[PDB]
Image (cartoon, rainbow over all chains, first blue to last red; front, side, top):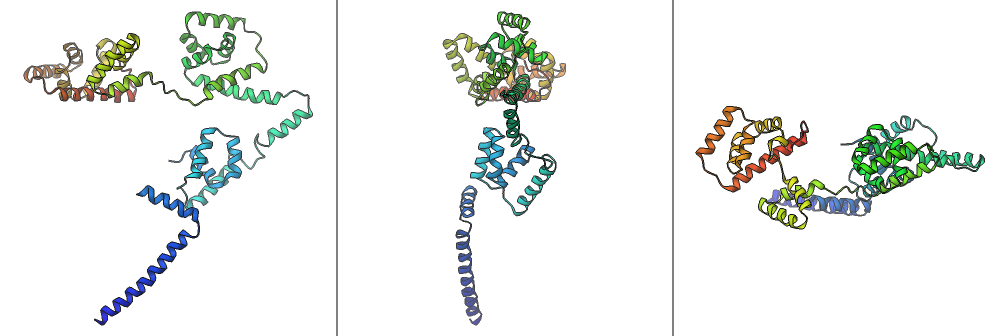
Length: 47
Length: 319
């Protein structure tokens, strides 16, 4: 299962990427707070 | 869609309050509040869109504005400065009222003559006389016809007496009349809408409310019943019109609605058939019995809907 272990290492890299994506989402929440509120309203309307 | 009004709206919501304030002071309340709402809720923003907006503004600046000095924005102030430097008489302000008055006179011509009359009936008969003189002759004749006989004769007599052709008092008179239509347009009277709403209701409840309003005021109930009326007698409905509608309307639908309709209605509707169609319809009326009243009313409502569609087309006067 060395390939499965490599897949687990890839999953750990994906988890680091997910943390970076979460940081990017946090950055979107952080910079342009107005734009974040506008996107909140837009997602609510799309909902 | 993006109209010339809408292009300016996008320009304003893109640029900001610095020019929005001048636009508001040169603008009207509903568009001011529309741009305020646009600022409050905006979802028309794009990297290319904003640049295109700036380009469109540059086009307006090089064409509509033609890179000119403030048009009546800061100029009116220098005009007031010259007025102050000259005799102590605000003629420029009177000309400003005259500008609104002349625009209001044109608006008066555009807008409904009877509404103009009832907005001016309460005012002075000399006001009516001078405004009718200053208005277009056709609009004046329309308002004259819509006046009652005595008020109309008094208006024309005071038109004959009208020789003062006054001078800034006339402008503010029109300004007052404009302010009496400047208020929110409303026009939600819907003289037809009661009738329209009752027609939109069920037919049995329609008849019940017709009886109720007959008890309330035979006049108002009769008006409501007239608003219900839609192609019930040939002479008012016009045969050419019965000819044109019912060839557009499905023959089977007409048949189903007619066998539930009164024999006079059947005869007046079939009088505009092609004779083969009339004979076929009458033969099938004899053959089949009255189908469910629900379906009969559905066909009648379809007939009325097609009448409304042709009324929308406006090629002829329905009834």
